[PDB]
Amino acid sequence: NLYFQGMKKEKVEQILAEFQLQEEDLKKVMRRMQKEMDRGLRLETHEEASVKMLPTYVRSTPEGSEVGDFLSLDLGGTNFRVMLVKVSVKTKHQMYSIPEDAMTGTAEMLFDYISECISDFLDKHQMKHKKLPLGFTFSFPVRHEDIDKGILLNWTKGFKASGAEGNNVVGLLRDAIKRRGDFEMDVVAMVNDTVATMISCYYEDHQCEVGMIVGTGCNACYMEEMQNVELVEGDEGRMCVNTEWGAFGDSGELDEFLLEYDRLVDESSANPGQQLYEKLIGGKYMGELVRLVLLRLVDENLLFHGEASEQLRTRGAFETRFVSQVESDTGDRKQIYNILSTLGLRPSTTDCDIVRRACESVSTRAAHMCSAGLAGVINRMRESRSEDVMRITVGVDGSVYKLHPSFKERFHASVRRLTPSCEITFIESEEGSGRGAALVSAVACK
Ligand SMILES: CS(=O)(=O)c1ccc([C@@H](C[C@H]2CCC(=O)C2)C(=O)Nc2cnccn2)cc1Cl
Ligand SMILES: OC[C@H]1O[C@H](O)[C@H](O)[C@@H](O)[C@@H]1O
Image 1 (cartoon, protein in one colour):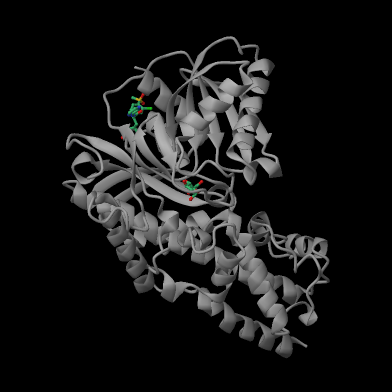
Image 2: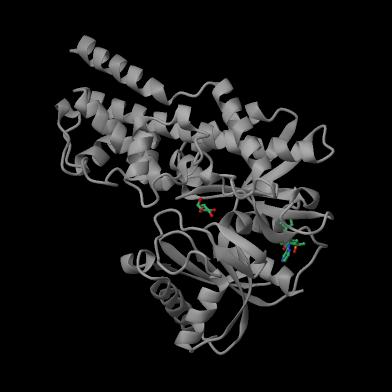
């Protein structure tokens, strides 16, 4: 019965319409983000600011860098990456899966693991004896005192290792290295992944002064005028600021836009009440948002005969990669069918179409919300600079931006609508977070 199949779809659409954000909604978000950014930069309001605008101590500096071998560490997904880079060739690269116990255990365990992975890598390439300059991409909010010293403000993205928050991260790393005592490293720089991504792209294209990650988490950094970074002495040149925009909304700034699914995701997360804007966008949460929408549709007898399988009712079962796979479906529904069948469902073609619409609704909202953030930053920059038309390059990494079949296109379109009088070039970084840490280390070394 097509009429009834059709009636189901119309009811689904009414439910999914909740995810829509009009252009004026996005402008509001953008303005509110810019407001929060202003607040993070100012001494008077930094402590209260949800968007921390953390100085990175990465500065505009004359051309050039030290040459040779640099080790780069990259922590901030569940995979830890070690990279040898010769200044530039990524001579060698190894990725290591972080055990469950290390991400939610003690900082000692986490950093012991990291140190072990480093010895493994140094062994695979017979260079454990060589004392190397090391750049550390550490993808969490850090309050820096310098390029090589900064305290972890709080874990995000489900990290929970005790004894890390409030401590110098470079010290934690150094301590773990010393405890193992089988190699030595000169940790010269610690940067955020947004920062590393920007640096890696900047190397290729000097117009790159913004980095953005849309991966497990979502964040951005940009080159701010020193005169605007009240938290650091000096008015000359530029310094990269790590926005930590994922925490936008943590003070209520997004309340009118948060849906029931968002509340649910937030409440089941490792950091309830935190990173709310990130929870609208990041790959850690996207598949779960879809899962909750699907459960709602099942509850309304709109999907899967009103029955959800064990798998569909399993936390994290609807993987963000499935959202990407569903929206990649060519129209034969074959990809969608296979995902849902593996989730223990017996989907009809209508079921498949509805799941497609759910995915599109969540991912479009993610794209649009993300666009308001980036537009806020770029518009801010254009204003801070003398600029009628600002031509700028944004370096981007992260599986959501890179792998989702239509996120990038929706995101770009929306950003462009919100940034007239800007000309934004987007570059997808290759090795960005790893390569960027080595590059910053080479510059920090000179
Ligand atoms: C000429 S360069 O490509 O070697 C280069 C120089 C400058 C820098 C800066 C960071 C860039 C990023 C965007 C921007 O406008 C400046 C750098 O490495 N700065 C730095 C490094 N260490 C300590 C303090 N500052 C990086 C790089 Cl790869
Ligand atoms: O990994 C992308 C982002 O994830 C989270 O938002 C982290 O707090 C931030 O530091 C990082 O840049």
